[PDB]
Every structure is written in structure tokens, then in C-alpha cells.
Amino acid sequence: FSIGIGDVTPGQGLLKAKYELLNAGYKKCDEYIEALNTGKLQQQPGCTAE
Amino acid sequence: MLLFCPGCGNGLIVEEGQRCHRFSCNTCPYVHNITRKVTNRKYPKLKEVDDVLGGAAAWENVDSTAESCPKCEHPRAYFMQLQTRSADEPMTTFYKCCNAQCGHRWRD
Ligand SMILES: [Zn+2]
Ligand SMILES: [Zn+2]
Image (cartoon, rainbow over all chains, first blue to last red; front, side, top):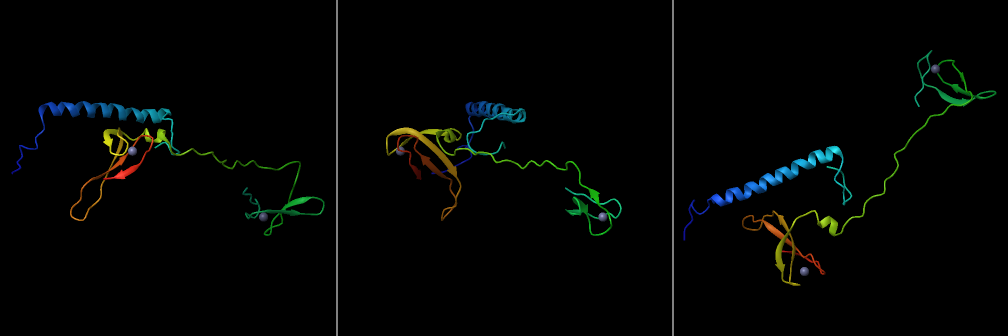
């Protein structure tokens, strides 16, 4: 029973799987900024804008 | 408000005189007549009515997962991730929530 560095290696088909997620996450998160600046984001909990 | 006297430079307090109320002070002789109307408008900040807390709408915020709960046979499951040090060496713990007609909370 042994462990090497070949055990933990990213797959080529895995690098583009998380690339899509990171791009969609960035595109979705960087919209709420100007959404708040314009005045939006209806709030369910009692809280402040930020 | 804040009113001072031009001659001396001190402040004034209003008190009764002979025929009508007067703007007086205790540092220099200076009295101004009180006439038809003197008043100022103030606007205290009025209270807001607050929100109702709790409900499934609040749980819509955090993301759930797909994992069975051995209490009511539902894939309905909310997951939580927290850090805490155990007795030997730290390991990330996770909380389990059932999104169903029972809705219990466990910590594995
Ligand atoms: Zn004075
Ligand atoms: Zn349950």
C-alpha cells in the first residue's frame, strides 16, 4: 500500500469541467454588483443591503 | 437652536418681562422683543416595521444537495460544512438537514 504524486493528478477532462463552473460563477457574481448599485435584490430576511 | 448676542458674544435664554416675554441674558444688557411668531421645524427619524424571520424562502438561499436521509426515505437534504478540531487532528464536519414533512437536524 503506497501513495505517490501520480495518485493526485487532475484529469484533462476535469480541467475544462471546473473552467465552465468558474466562468459561470464569475459572470453571475459580477452582476449583483451593478444590480445593487442600480437598486435591486429584493430581500426575504430582515437585513441590510450588503 | 443656538443663538448668541452680537454685543457681548454669549448666549441668551428667554424669560418673562413686564408686558411680554423677552430674550434675555446674564452677561450684558440686551433684550429683543418677541413678535408675531418664532418657531423651528424638527423631524425625528420615524420607526420602521421589521420583517418576518424564518421559513422555506430563507432556506432557498443556501444550496442543498441530493442525499438520502435514513428517517423518512427522502433524497431531500440540505448540507452544511463547518470546521472544528477533534481530539487528534482537525477534520471538516458536516451538518445534515431534512427538507420534508418532518424536517430534523443532525450532525454526523
Ligand atoms: Zn448677551
Ligand atoms: Zn427527515
